[PDB]
Length: 152
Image (cartoon, rainbow, N blue to C red; front, side, top):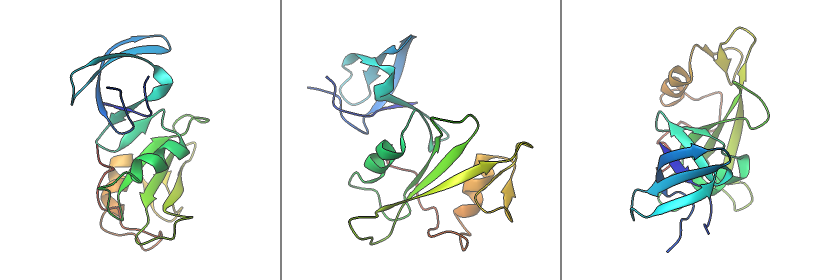
């Protein structure tokens, strides 16, 4: 349901799966699902996850960090809500055999004022689930077929 984003403060690290115990303002209480240890951490150091690939509070930079962890093949992907906008998202997908200076490709997921979502205006979707479904099988309009969700 949640993931640690950085070193804190024997310690948590990026990608570590979490269980949220309390959300008291900008400080959350979490449990690591590998060590069981309890942590009192700033909310900004944690990302919420739903649908196995939908992240909240995950920056563009931290998304690259997550996707670039070992064990993520080419096509590994996630969707992250914009930290600037509302129901606006970005698709981040690991590139296959990339050069070191461009290993991750980000696509804006446009949401019209009508609530439908798309990367290419020719192909619109009623939900992120429908979008991921589609691009897991057909992805000619983008760089990469969506293979697997980012590890954890």
